[PDB]
Length: 14
Image (cartoon, rainbow, N blue to C red; front, side, top):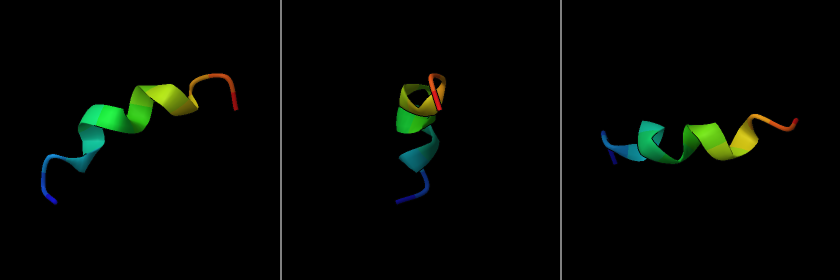
């Protein structure tokens, strides 16, 4: 779970 930031860029358009 600590590695969840790896998906954060997907939110860039929002």
